[PDB]
Length: 186
Ligand SMILES: [Fe+3]
Image 1 (tube, helix red, strand yellow):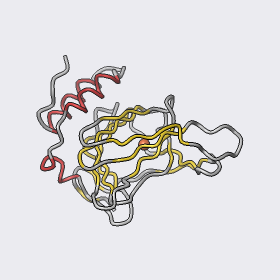
Image 2: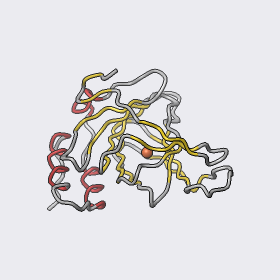
Image 3: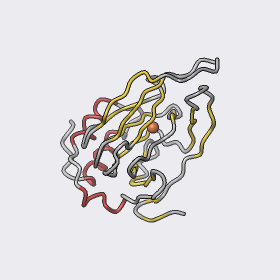
């Protein structure tokens, strides 16, 4: 029985219910995330930027089965092409716009990775990826506006792979946190 989250806090409570069992209903989770209307005051605490690259800010640790974070993207900031370590990944825009470029898993052969597609994710939209769908890059292409996104990962994971667009070669990356619960974590 899915209800609209009134606030980020409400959203988080609802996520604990949704993940109360062993199986994830992806469409339900995506629906509730989308239904949350971004309110900058509610997440300002987590929206910590860095001048040179995008940041990952932990919001909620979940119930063992997921966690929830906020990512902050300066003008021109973006990610590698990457996977998500056999986890569900939900991405919702809270401010600005992000360009998401989808790539297929590379064949064993060293080849240029060619874009399957791209789309512009706009404020409040929720996108979903998992490894069975493919790989992606996410970028703030704006010259004038920062972007902020809300991400849900299930199960949680702290490692992933980055892919070189020229070759498809991957490298294992350990992902870090800029902050946890509003507290900067050097
Ligand atoms: Fe990603």
